[PDB]
Length: 108
Image (cartoon, rainbow, N blue to C red; front, side, top):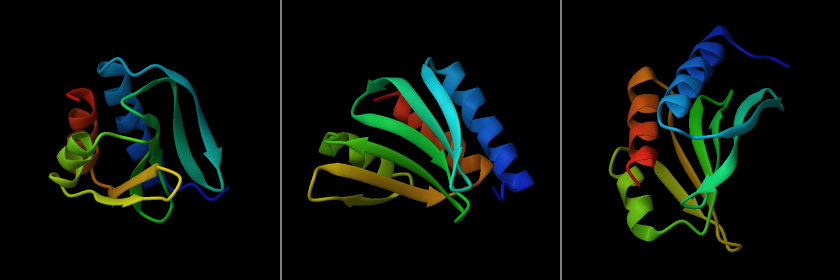
């Protein structure tokens, strides 16, 4: 795996905020050099929060509510809804964005 120091720092912040807001994690994986925080208790369609080596923080979900998606795009996240209903929300990694993203996910 090729995990950078920035990724570790970003993942640490992500985990800190996920714990703060009561998101229960089954585990965190390092897969294809990406960090995946896998939710044990899926909420509002969200399956995992990710810190990817491509520079983005991503939310992987399934059949999320449109008005929920709107709150994420409202803070700068890009969104792609697949034919199967899977939703991919992306935004560039930064302390500010990680904080903003988790805050929104917590107020859903």
